[PDB]
Image (spheres, coloured by chain):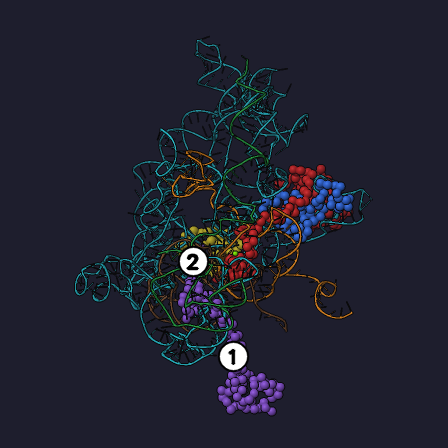
Chain colours: A red, B yellow, C blue, D purple, E green, F brown, G orange, H cyan
Amino acid sequence: LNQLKSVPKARNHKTKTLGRGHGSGLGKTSGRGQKGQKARKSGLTRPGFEGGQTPLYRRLPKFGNARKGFLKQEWVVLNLNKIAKLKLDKINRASLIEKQVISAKSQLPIKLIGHTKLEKPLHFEVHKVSKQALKAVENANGSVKLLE
Amino acid sequence: VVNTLNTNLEQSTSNIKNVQVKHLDKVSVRDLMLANALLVEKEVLKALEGKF
Amino acid sequence: MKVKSAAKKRFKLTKSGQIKRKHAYTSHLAPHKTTKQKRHLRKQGTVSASDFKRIGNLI
Amino acid sequence: MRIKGGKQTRVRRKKWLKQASGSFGTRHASYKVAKQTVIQAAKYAYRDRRNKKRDFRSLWILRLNAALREQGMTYSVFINLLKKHNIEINRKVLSELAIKEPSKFNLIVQKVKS
RNA sequence: AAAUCCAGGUACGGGUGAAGACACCCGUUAGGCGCAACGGGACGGAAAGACCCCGUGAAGCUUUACUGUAGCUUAAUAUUG
RNA sequence: UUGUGGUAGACGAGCGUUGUAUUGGAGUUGAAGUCAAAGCGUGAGCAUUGGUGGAUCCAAUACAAGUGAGAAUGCCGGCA
RNA sequence: AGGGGUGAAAUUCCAAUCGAAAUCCGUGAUAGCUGGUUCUCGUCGAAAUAGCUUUAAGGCUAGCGUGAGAUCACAAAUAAG
RNA sequence: GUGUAGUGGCGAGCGAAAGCGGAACAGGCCAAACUUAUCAUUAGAUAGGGGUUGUAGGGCUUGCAAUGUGGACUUGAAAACGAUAGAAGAAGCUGUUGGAAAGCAGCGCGCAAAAGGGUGAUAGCCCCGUAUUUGAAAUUGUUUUCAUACCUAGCGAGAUCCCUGAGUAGCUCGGAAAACGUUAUUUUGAGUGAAUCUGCCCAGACCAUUGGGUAAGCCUAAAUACUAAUUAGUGACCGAUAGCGAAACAGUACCGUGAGGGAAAGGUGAAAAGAACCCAGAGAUGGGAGUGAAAUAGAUUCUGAAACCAUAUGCCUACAACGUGUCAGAGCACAUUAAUGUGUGAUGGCGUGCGUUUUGAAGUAUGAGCCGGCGAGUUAUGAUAGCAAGCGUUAGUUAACCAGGAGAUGGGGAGCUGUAGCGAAAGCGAGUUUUAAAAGAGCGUUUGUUUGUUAUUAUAGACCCGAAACGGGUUGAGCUAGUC
Ligand SMILES: [Mg+2]
Ligand SMILES: [Mg+2]
Ligand SMILES: [Mg+2]
């Protein structure tokens, strides 16, 4: 690129120098306004604040948490709207790791889902399937095996 | 650019400020486009093709 | 930033913005509010555009 | 890196000082007063660039009325005899300068008497 | 030496003006520069008003303001039969 | 063709500084710093010659900022 | 010998300073309160209002500015009815 | 993991433990039974052997198999690589400008040595060095080898036998550490106080089942934190108001009784070749002379700006109401970055500074005496939005760490964002929540990630400077007050 002269396409934006004269704008006040609280150093009061008035978040009641102190048991999900693009049969753990859909260092239950039609038959052994997802995958003359 | 990093050549060319010998994996974009002249050696063509 | 602890317990963040919230005026006094008010305030709504920016950057 | 910047300040204040010469007292010595004097002088120049074309017109009017009063008519009557009839687009700077070379402006004052 | 000082070549009357003008508008007077005086003015100098008010300022003090506490006092308990 | 006053402020386009990296170049036949002059640009600014001074400096493209000074009863130094 | 001392008691004295010494440290204490904040040109360009606020010299939202984008016609202004 | 679970006048805020990916890797030793010896053997004590624990182990009886591997380990001997001084260490002349050549030009040469410094101006070949090769009488470091102590050694059968850390664990009342603001867990001031392998403790009250682990004894290198010190080196670090306060005889001068506070300041020349000698003057000194390329380099010692002070060429000024200029305008004197030139300005018209803060300032509001220098929107880590780039529809992308010249980069898929959302939640699923309702309503029925740059913002002092104060530690009764 002839280092004696190298150029980008477009990245050099106007830099707002705050204390550099009225000619450029941003004169003595540096864009802080005129003699307010913001104008003083360390202005811009606490993010959630409405000047003494009860702030919005403090007025509203709290959402409850029924299952308290627990983490929702995560699921790994195969949506049929995209699995067709993944050309593979006998979908299982021994294969999904090769396609890098899931990772080897993961012992997690596998769930099936989706309403879209699918053309070529497939085969799964998973833990849960939706009702109409099972109907759709069976209508394609596929199969599914329910692992506990 | 070189693969085996011969020592006869590396021992030479050391005092010559303009020249420099670098391994195939030691060269950078700046270290290459600054040369304006280089002598690639015979085999690294295949390795460069593989690495693309 | 540390998420404001008093914010995440009132604002379930829904898909594509539109922060959700419960309604107030539902915790203390029953008789002073009519059944119309009582069965409208039980449902939840979003936050208006005025406070949407100030709440979104707080979460 | 740390920057001192001695040349630029000296050059700038030298230019500002040089803009003002012949000024009384310390005005031509101290930059802090020289800049203010240059501002005021340029304001005065901007005002007088309009004032001078406002005033030379009046000067022409005066030196034309003075000549016209020696022929037996006033300046106000003159313009009508130019405008309404014997139409001319003769400016007031030459309708005033022509008196300085007379016997030709009297042709103007007599032509309008028709 | 000293405090002081935006640059000055620094008149008076009527009026105007951020509301009492050396500089403005209209008039009147006034050769340039000293020295000794005397203090009317330059809202003359020194002192970010000590009075008054504001600050969700400070300190000191007071009490049947609030919350505590040193101390004093009473009980249970170990030393204790 | 419509315009082109402007404080707070919003946006765009630029000048200058010191250093770094690439090319190019100048310099005891006198560089930089300094002064002078009746030079040139829309503006930040940029030249030309002469005196002094005696050893580094300039141009093009990017990058990096301890980068631009009239005011803070500012500090320091000098002189009224 | 200092949230201490001393006081024939005045808020006296404690190294020219005392309603609580001097010096160092936490310390670049905080300040909704003053003052300061430095190069250029071009385009556009307000508000001093409403509600709430231990709020009134402050703040949040709305109102008014500006940049990007959309709506061109059913939207918005201008006359007549 | 993550700003997650949680904790919080549920306010300000605070913030894990698992799990995963990495750096490093070593586990041993006592008490106790049992037994030997010695203690007025009342041992209830001392010194030996034995044993060091969870798929419970050890002791007790009776056997089998072993002579080893290993040390967080003793002595010497040997080897190796260093550390503390050094030695060798290539290559050039001529000409010109010049005071001086090393500049520049012409013709050559060396290179495992074109780092640096000096040499009268910028030297690969003038010198010291450099790359490279070598060098230890003496002290000392590290590792390896040999022998050498000390420690260290497996597997069976029997049998209600014994031992397994007591003012201990728990429990009560007060506190605290753990992310918790007293809560399972840990800790303790007062009190109280067990069990012994069918045991005891634990799996955020508590009980049962299941499972995990065996407290109330001790020690242990590596990854880790730091750099006043030594050696080498580096810098898009400072260059005499900067950089440590201190480039120099700096914690000095100076102030304070004392704790303590605490500055300023450099450069002749190439080498003194520091100005013999003459004049003036008492002398300092100045003018000559001399050295010197330069004496307007002369010790005041590189460069020398402005404020300020003087002197002079040209023009103007002593009837003049002046924010001092401006637009016109003679006269006068000159000749330039050749330009409808410059210098001055009798005279005419007009004309109440600069920044601040204000509804409104020439202001009888405020700040600056002038000049010069220093002096205020930064950085770390995040989030948001704009612009552009890379890769893209089972996408994108690394972190720590390792290797790489304190480089780009390669390895590292641990994670992160997106791919399906709704619901407080279990759950369901292109649906889901509410609901008797599949009605109705709310949310959804697809647009990405990693960067660079800009702007804004959050925690950090977070544009600059300015308090009276607050809390802790020290120095002060030499003045003054009281007392002896
Ligand atoms: Mg300013
Ligand atoms: Mg201000
Ligand atoms: Mg006064």
Does residue C15 appear in this view?
A: no
Q: Residue at x 53, y 79 (%)?
A: D58
> Measured from the top left, where is residue H231 in percent x and y?
36, 45
Where in the figure is residue E9, as x and y percent of width and height?
41, 68
Residue visible at 43% across and 59% down in the picture: D5
- Tell which of H227 and H171 is nearer to you: H171
Q: Nearer the viewer, residue D72 or F21?
A: D72
Q: Amino acid at mark 1?
A: Phe
Task: Provide the chain ID for the residue under circle 1.
Answer: D
Label count reads 2
Q: Which mark is residue D4?
A: 2
Q: Quadrant of the C terminus of chain A?
A: top right
Q: Secondary structure at mark 2?
A: loop
The disc label shown at residue A38, or none:
none
Instruction: From the top left corner, tell me how far across and down residue C24 is, in percent.
Output: 70, 45
The relative height of residue H26 versus residue A88 in the rendered view (above or below) is above
Front in this rendered view, residue H267 or H419: H267
At a point 56% along the width and 91% down the height, the residue shown is D110
Classify 10 Å Cα crowding around label 2: few (below 14), some (14-19), many (20 and above): few
> How far apart in space, not on screen, are marks 2 and 1 (Cα)?
52 Å
Residue H432 shown left or right of residue H226 in the figure: right
Residue H199 drawn above or below residue B49 = above
Which label number is shown at residue D56? 1
Disc 1, SS: helix
